[PDB]
Image (tube, rainbow, N blue to C red; front, side, top):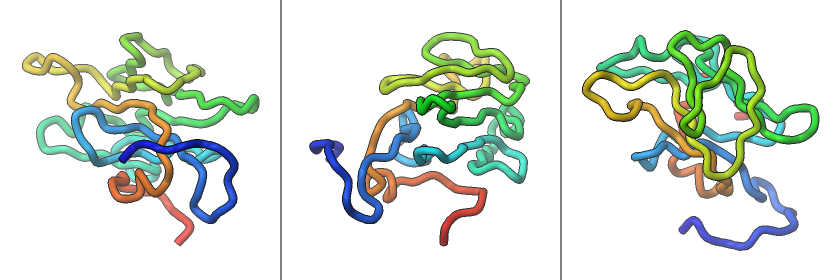
Length: 145
């Protein structure tokens, strides 16, 4: 799939919903609901938790936080990242605003000595809820059950 026309919305769970397509995989898609803060990390309390067996320490609680600035545009901000956050082959700063767009690359942390690119990689893409629903990400925070 991943194809269709965009226009007016008039149906429950309709319209489009941005997200972070996991580069290299077809799962763990972090939904980016318009007007909904998305905090990723490992510590309990974040909307998205990421735990691994190889290097689970590589990620820290609240490694990053997405949100649409008062203007109405999505902006990725790093909550004082320790290892550092990368965006489109660029280093990010702590507590900074970065306007993202379709075709981006968010990297949580730095690559290893035996890994060309960071294990965790995503891509800002706009996909309907019915498209990311099937392959959604592990939500650690609350939700409208």
